[PDB]
Amino acid sequence: EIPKPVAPAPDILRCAYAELVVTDLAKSRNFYVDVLGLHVSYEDENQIYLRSFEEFIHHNLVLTKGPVAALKAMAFRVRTPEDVDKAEAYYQELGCRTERRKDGFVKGIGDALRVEDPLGFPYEFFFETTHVERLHMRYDLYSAGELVRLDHFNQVTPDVPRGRKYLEDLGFRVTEDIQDDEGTTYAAWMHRKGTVEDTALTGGNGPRLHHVAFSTHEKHNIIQICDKMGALRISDRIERGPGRHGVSNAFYLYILDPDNHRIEIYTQDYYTGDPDNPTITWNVHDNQRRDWWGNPVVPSWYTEASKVLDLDGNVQEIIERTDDSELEVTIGADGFSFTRAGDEDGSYHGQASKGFKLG
Amino acid sequence: IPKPVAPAPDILRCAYAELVVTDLAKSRNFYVDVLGLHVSYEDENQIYLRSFEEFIHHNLVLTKGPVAALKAMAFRVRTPEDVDKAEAYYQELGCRTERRKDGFVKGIGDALRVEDPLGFPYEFFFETTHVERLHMRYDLYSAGELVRLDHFNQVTPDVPRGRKYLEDLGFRVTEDIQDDEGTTYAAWMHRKGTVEDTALTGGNGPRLHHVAFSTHEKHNIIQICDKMGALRISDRIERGPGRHGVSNAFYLYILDPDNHRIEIYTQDYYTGDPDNPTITWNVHDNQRRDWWGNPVVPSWYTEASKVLDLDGNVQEIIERTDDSELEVTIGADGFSFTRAGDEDGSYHGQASKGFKLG
Amino acid sequence: EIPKPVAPAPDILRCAYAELVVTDLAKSRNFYVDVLGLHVSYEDENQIYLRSFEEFIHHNLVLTKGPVAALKAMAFRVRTPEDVDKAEAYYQELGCRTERRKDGFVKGIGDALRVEDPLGFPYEFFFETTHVERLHMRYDLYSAGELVRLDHFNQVTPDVPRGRKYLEDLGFRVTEDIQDDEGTTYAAWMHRKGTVEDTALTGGNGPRLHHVAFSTHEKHNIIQICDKMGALRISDRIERGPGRHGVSNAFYLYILDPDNHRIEIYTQDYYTGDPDNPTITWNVHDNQRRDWWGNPVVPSWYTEASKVLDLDGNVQEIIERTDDSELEVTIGADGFSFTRAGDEDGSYHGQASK
Amino acid sequence: EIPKPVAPAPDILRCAYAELVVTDLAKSRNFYVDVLGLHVSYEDENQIYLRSFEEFIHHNLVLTKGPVAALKAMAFRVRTPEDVDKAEAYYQELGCRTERRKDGFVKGIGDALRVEDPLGFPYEFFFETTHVERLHMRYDLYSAGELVRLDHFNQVTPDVPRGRKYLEDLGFRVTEDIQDDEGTTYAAWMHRKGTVEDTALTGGNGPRLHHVAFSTHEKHNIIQICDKMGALRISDRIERGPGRHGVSNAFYLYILDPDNHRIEIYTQDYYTGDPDNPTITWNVHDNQRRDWWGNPVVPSWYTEASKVLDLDGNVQEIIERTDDSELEVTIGADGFSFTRAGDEDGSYHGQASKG
Ligand SMILES: [Ca+2]
Ligand SMILES: [Cl-]
Ligand SMILES: [Cl-]
Ligand SMILES: [Cl-]
Ligand SMILES: [Cl-]
Ligand SMILES: [Fe+2]
Ligand SMILES: [Fe+2]
Ligand SMILES: [Fe+2]
Ligand SMILES: [Fe+2]
C-alpha cells in the first residue's frame, strides 16, 4: 500500500501530452500526420511535435526517434508554477526518483518535473508551455476525421487497487470501475478535468502503456477514420471497434501505430466534475461493460501494450499480475459472460460473444 | 434457366415482405417498439408496417403462423398490365403461379404469387392502397428511424444460375464476389438505381438471408445498437455496425424474435445508368464484406430463414456444392488478406482481429 | 403552348453535367476545387473539368473561360446512343435550333446534341462518355464537406405551366409544386432518376439558370461547408441557409461562386420512382414551404440568376414573367405568409418572417 | 465598482439549475416535456422538476406556476457544504440581501443560499442535492432531439465591465468577449466548469435573463428540434438559428417557450479549464462574431429578455443601459458590420446582413 504523503499533492489540471519513442520517424509521421491529421507544431530529424485541432499549448504528442519503442513520459499540466515544486516534494516523500529541468525535457515545455512514479510510470508535471495558434475554428483545415483534443492515457499495472489509492491521494477521482464478486478489481478510470478519465488503470503485467486517447467532435468522425484506413488498405491496423463503451459511454475506436503503440479515438462521454459524481461499478462478466453492443474484445487488447521507460531511458522491468485476468475470466477456457444477469440465454461459457473463440 | 419468349414484367423495386412469425405480440414489440416501424393495419392475425418515407400501404406484413418463414417477397411493377406479363413469364418458365384479383394481403390489389425457379415465393403487384406519407412527420421521428425498404437477400446454392435468371427478369448486377478459380460466392442486383433490390448469397437454399431497411444517417444505425444495449438485447445484434465493401453502405444486422435477420443500411451509391461499372471482389479480400476488416460472424454465413411454397409449406433445401465462403475465408483451411499478395495483415485458418470460429 | 412531337422522346436517365462560363478561371478553380473539394477530371488554361465523389462518368461540371459568365449547357444523359438521334428528331419537330457533334462539345463526352429549347435553355443530350475512376470508396480523399453526386438543375422561366407541360412530354414527372388558390403556379419540381428533381422550374424572368445542385451524404457535411466559408472569411458568399426545405424535404444550403453562379448543396430527399408517386402542392403563402423552419427567403434568391447562352455563345434575351411574383405575394409590401393557415399569430404581412 | 470582499469566494463547480416562473403549467409541460423531451424528476400541481439525459442531481430546471413569468433563481452548485457558508459570508460583505434554508427552497436541493446579487439577479448556491437515476445510457428513452446537459445561463445587464469584475472576483474566468475600438464592452462569457461559459453577460437593460442553454451530443440533434417544430407547426417559436456561433464556436439554436423564456440549444464548444486559457476578443462590427456564417441577428434577440425576481418574488426594476447598443451599432439605421476587416465588399451599412 502506497502511503499518503504529508506534503500536499500538486493541483493537476489534465492530461496534456505523451512523449512516445518511435523507431522510424518518417513512418510514424505518416501515421499521425498523413493518416490521422494531427497538426505539426515543430519537427526536425529527431522529433515531431503534434497537437490536436482545439489545443493552444505547444503539443499533445511528441514523437522522439530512438532504438526501442516505448512511452518516455506521460505529462500532466498543473495549475501553477508552484505546483511543480509541490509535485517534486510529493514524489520525494513517496521515495520516488525525480528529475527537474528548469527549461524542460522537450521543446515548448518550460520548467518540468519527471518522476518514476510508484507504479513505475514516467510521469511529467509542468505548468510553463509555449502557446501556439489555437486551430479550433480553422475549418479550412478540418479533416473529416479530425482529432480535436487529447483526452486520456491508459496504464497497465498488475495491482489495480494499489494504483487507485495512490491516484486518489494525488487528487484523481474514480468515475467507473470493473470488479467481480470475489474482491478483484480489473480496471478503474479516474479524472481531474471533469470527464470520465485523464488516466486509467487496466489490470495486467506492467508498467506498460495501454493507449493514448484523442477525441473527435462526432461519431461520424470516428467512422471516417475507419473508412480512411480501409481506403489506405491498412485495416489490419484497426485493432478493435468502432463501438459504444459501457464504461464511459463513449463511442470509441482502437488503432495501432507503426511501433504498435495503441491509440484510442473517443467521443461523447459525460460530465464528472461534481465531487460526489456517482462511481459506476460494472461486473467483469457483464458482456456490455466494454462494448455496450456486446461485441467481443479481441485478446490483443488485453495482452499487448507498450513498454515504458525510466528516467535513464531504459525499459522498466515488467511485474506480473497475480490477480485474476479479465481475459481469462470472460473469454478464456473457464471464462463466462452474460447479456442479462441471471439469464442463461445470451450467456457465453468458455468463449467470446458473437460466435468467436480465442485464436 | 431459359429466357422466355414472353416479355419480362417491368419491375420498379422491392416493395414488401410477408414474414410468418410465431408470436405476434413479441414480433410487434420488436418491429414497432424497438425498431419504430409505423402501423398501417393490425389485427389478431397480422401486423402491417411501413417505413417513415413510404406511401404504399406497407413494407412488411407479419403474419401469425405455426412455422416462421418467408411467405412472400414482393416487387412492385410499373403498370397493371405488368402483372399479366409476370403471369405469362412465369407460366412459360413452367413455374407454379397463383393470381388473386383482390390481393393476398390487405392494401394490395391484383397480385400474382409464384414459386420461382429458385424455389422463392415472389409476388408481383401494381395496385396498392396509398397511406399518409410520413416523411415530414418529425414529431414521430425516432433517433433510429427506418426510412425506406431497401432490399432482400436470398440464399441459393448456385449463384450464376440465379444471376442469369434475374438478369433476364431485368435486374442488373452491380457487385459480386468471386475467386480466381471461377467460383461465384455472391451477387447483388437492382432495378431502382441503388446497389440492390435483391441479392444472392451462395449457400444451401432456398432460404431468406435478410430484409434490409435504410436510415438517413449513420448515427441512426448507431442508435439502434445503443437502444438494443439499453434494452439488454445486445445478443440480438448479430453483426456490425460496419462499413460494407460491396455496396459501400454503412450497416448492421440484427435478429427478430423468430431469428429472421434484418439489415439496417445507409448510403450506398447510384447505379441507374445502364453501363454502371460492375465491381468484382475477391473472396479472400478481408475488406470485401466489412471494409474495416472486422470478422464476419459464422452465423451470418450459416443461418437464414425458411421459405414457403404457395400452400404455406416449407420449401425443401438443396445443398450448395460450390465452395463455401465461410470455409475458404475463416474456417481452419481458410484465408483472407488485407493487401493482396501481402502476408502481413493476412489471416490463415482463423478470422481477422485475433478470433477463430467458436 | 408547346405541342407534343409525334417523334418519340429521348429516354433521359438523369441530369449529368453543366458547362458554366466563368470570367477568371483561377478564381473559379479556387472556389470549386479548393473550397468545395470537387475532383479534377481534366484541366488546361481554358477549362477545368470536375466531378463529384461517387461519379464514374467523365465530369459533372465544366468551367470554361469566357468573356461573360453564363450557363453554356445543361446536360442530360440518355439511355442509349440512339436516344441522341431521338432527341435530334424531337427538337427539330419542335422547331428548335440544334447542333450535333459526333465527337462532343467538351472533353470526355462523345456524340452529343445541343439545342436551344423552347424555353430558351441550352440543353445537351448525350450517351457516350469516358468513364473515370469512381472515387466512392476513396476515403483518403474524402473532405469534411464532400460533394458526392450531381443532383439537379433549377431554371427560371416566366410561365411555369407552359414549361411544365413541355417537360412532362419529355418524360419528367412532377413531384412537387407551389400554387395559390387563384390558380397561379410559382414553381414545379420534376424528375427522371427517382429523386425529387432532375430539373425544376422557378417562376421569374427567363431563361436564366437559378442553380446547380450537388448532394452530400449527411447534414454535417453541409454544416462543414458553411463553417469552412466562415474560416475563409467568405461568409458573404453564403446566400441562404443552411435549412430544411419544405418542398423536397431536403437539407440545403445556397452559396455563390465568383461569377455569382448559385450552387445548392442538398441531402436527403425521398424516393419518387413509382409512377403514381403522390404529388405535393404547397400554398405560396405557407411560410414552411421553402424553409420548413420558417426562416425568411432573402429577396436575392428570387431576383438573381445566371444568364444563359444560345448555341453561338451569345446571351439569351430575357422574357419578363407576367404571372404573379412569389416574392411580391409573400415578402413584398402587399405580401403575406402564415405558419398555420388561418392563424394571424405567426403570420407575416408586408414583411418577411422572424 | 463592486469591491472585492475580504471573505474568500465560494468554490463554484458549475451552473446546476434554473427556477422559472411560468403562467400555465400544462402548456409549459407540453413545451419542455413533449416538444423538447426533458425528463420529469418530480411533478405536482404547482411545479415540474426536469432534468437532462446525463444529469444525476435532482434537476436542471424547475417550472414554478405563478402570476408573472420570470427567472426566480439561477443556481450554481458549490464543491462542499462549507462553500455554502463561504457564499453567505461573501454576499453579506458585499451588502447583498441573503436568505439561507437548511432544507432547500425547491425539492431535491438541501441547504441552499439565495441572494439578490450586486447586479439584481437571484443567485442560489447549494451543495446538497438528492441524486436520481442518471439516464445517460437509457437509449430506450433517447430522443432524436435529446437534451443531454444544462450548459449555461446568459444575463442581460447594463454595464458589462462592472459585472465582469464582480464575476471574476467570484472565480469565473472570462473566455470570450465583444468590444469595439472606442472602449465599449457589449458582452462577456465566463466559466467555472471548463467550458466556454457557465454564465454570460449581454449588454442591455437589466437585470433580465437572456436565456438558459442546454447541450445536445451532436449537431443533427439540434436540426431535429427545428424539424420537429416545423412538423408541429410551431416554427414561429424558432427565434434564431440554427447556426454556428463565432463566440464559443458552438452549434446553436434559440427558441421561445410559452412565456417567451428563451432557450438555447448548444453543442461542441471547447475546453477552457487551463488558467491561462487564451481570451478571445471580437470586434462588435465583425459579422461573423455571433453567427459565424454571417446570418443576421434578429432584433428581438437583442431587445427581448425575461424578467427576474427578488427574494420576495417581486419583479426587479429594470435599469437602462447607457453604453452603446449592440443592435444599434450593427443593424440599426446607423449600424455597420463587415465580413472582412477593412473590406467594403461584404460590409453592411444601416442594415442587417443577407439582404
Ligand atoms: Ca465470481
Ligand atoms: Cl473497453
Ligand atoms: Cl457483407
Ligand atoms: Cl426553396
Ligand atoms: Cl450569439
Ligand atoms: Fe481509453
Ligand atoms: Fe444486404
Ligand atoms: Fe434546388
Ligand atoms: Fe448562450
Image (tube, coloured by chain):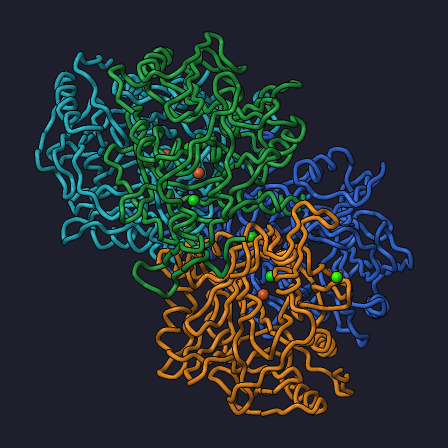
Chain colours: A orange, B green, C cyan, D blue
Front in this rendered view, residue A247 or C48 = A247
Query: Compared to B133, does C104 lie above or below?
Result: below
* Residue D9 visible in the picture: yes
The furthest residue to the top: B101
Residue B176 location (% of width, % of height): 33, 41
Q: Which residue does the image show at 21% across and 51% down from the upper left?
A: C24
Q: Relative to residue C35, is residue B357 drawn left or right? A: right
Q: Which residue does the image show at 51% across and 30% down from the upper left?
A: B306
Residue A118 location (% of width, % of height): 67, 84
* Residue D213 visible in the picture: no
The furthest residue to the right: D102
Front in this rendered view, residue C60 or C161 = C60
Count of numbered circles in the view: 0
Residue C85 location (% of width, % of height): 12, 24
Q: Which residue does the image show at 62% across and 51% down from the upper left?
A: D215
Query: Compared to D174, does B219 lie above or below?
Result: above
Query: Compared to A159, does B307 lie above or below?
Result: above
Front in this rendered view, residue A339 or A253 = A339
Q: Relative to residue D241, is residue D306 drawn left or right? A: right
Question: Quadrant location of residue D197?
Answer: bottom right
Front in this rendered view, residue A303 or C211 = A303
Question: Quadrant location of residue A193?
Answer: bottom right
Question: Quadrant location of residue B85?
Answer: top left
Residue A347 location (% of width, % of height): 66, 50
What is the quadrant of the N terminus of chain A in the image? bottom right
